[PDB]
Amino acid sequence: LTPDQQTLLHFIMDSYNKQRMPQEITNKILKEEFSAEENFLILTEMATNHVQVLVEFTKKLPGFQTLDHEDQIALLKGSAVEAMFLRSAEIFNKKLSGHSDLLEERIRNSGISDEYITPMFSFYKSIGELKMTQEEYALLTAIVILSPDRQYIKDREAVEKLQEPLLDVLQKLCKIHQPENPQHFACLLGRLTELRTFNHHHAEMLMSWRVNDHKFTPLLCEIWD
Amino acid sequence: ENALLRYLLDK
Ligand SMILES: O=C(O)c1cc(F)c2nc(N3[C@@H]4CC[C@H]3C[C@@H](OCc3c(-c5ccccc5OC(F)(F)F)noc3C3CC3)C4)sc2c1
């Protein structure tokens, strides 16, 4: 419904495909030896790159540049882990460039504990059967980044004033493309709680990695402390 | 203190 949603939606869809991952980074999932060392480095590169495309994508979300500035950093630092999941989920499920079956092994031998690899791909498979469209991936990303519930937020109501419209547009989209089962909107929103569970375990993977001398880029260090 | 995040939010 409404035309004003289209002015808000497609402009978000403008930003969601403005930048893909550079070919200079994706092609080494193929070209280079499958070492536990180089596996981690490639993943570091892509994670490094993805923080950049997210900051640009969020910088355009309507009303983001108007928020307080000590809170936008808390928005980014609290959502970067989860938004990287959505994009890599869209890659694994659509099987796009991402080199799915080869990227997954490079992930499976990067020093990650087995108790974190199992629930990770169970998520990947589960969110694949949802047969989600690109606009659903794009909005869910916007809603995750603009989460008023994040840690060290001061003006929590300000975030709600910009997350609320995008939530209504999305449920008004499970109106058109699926009128058969009204629960699809509640099924996409479950994923955002799934991602929160992962954000808990991700802090553990990080400390396990640097225990073992895994240097990150300066920017991942800043966004994960 | 959020040196690099603030730089990309202003580029
Ligand atoms: O636009 C495209 O075409 C495109 C193609 C891709 F192929 C692709 N791939 C992506 N991504 C995201 C999340 C998994 C996959 C690889 C990166 O994550 C690496 C990572 C994570 C990580 C963070 C969140 C989720 C999974 C993660 O990796 C993990 F190993 F599974 F844990 N933590 O540390 C790290 C590296 C060591 C420092 C960024 S985005 C992306 C975009």
Image (cartoon, coloured by chain):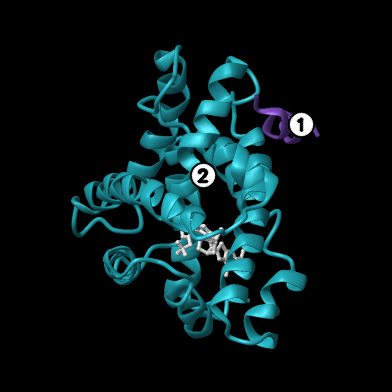
Chain colours: A cyan, B purple
The answer to whether mark 2 and mark 1 are in CB contact below 8 A is no
Residue A113 relative to residue A51: left or right: left
Is the residue B7 above or below the residue A25 in the image? above
Which chain letter goes with mark 2?
A
Is any part of residue A3 visible from this angle?
no
- Residue that appears at 65% across and 28% down: B2
Residue A32 to residue B1: above or below:
below
The residue at label 2 has a CB less than 8 Å from ligand 1:
no
Q: Secondary structure at mark 1?
A: helix
Q: Quadrant of residue A127?
A: bottom left
Give the letter of the chain under mark 1.
B
Q: Which residue is mark 1?
A: B7
Mark 2 neighbour class, 10 Å CA radius: few under 14, some 14 to 19, many 20 or more: many
Q: Name the quarter where the C terminus of chain A is drawn.
A: top right
Q: Which residue is mark 2?
A: A80
Residue A61 in sight from this viewpoint: yes
Q: CA distance from mark 2 to mark 1?
A: 17 Å
Mark 2 secondary-structure assignment: helix
> Which amino acid type is marked by label 2?
Ala
The amino acid marked with disc number 1 is Tyr
Task: Tell me if mark 1 has few (under 14), some (14-19) or many (20+) residues whose alpha carbon lies within 10 angstroms of its own.
Answer: few
Residue A100 horizontal side relative to residue A55, left or right: left
Q: Could you tell me residue A152's position as x and y percent? A: 43, 20
Q: Nearer the viewer, residue A68 or A172?
A: A68
Give the left or right position of residue A175, taking residue A98 as reference. Answer: left
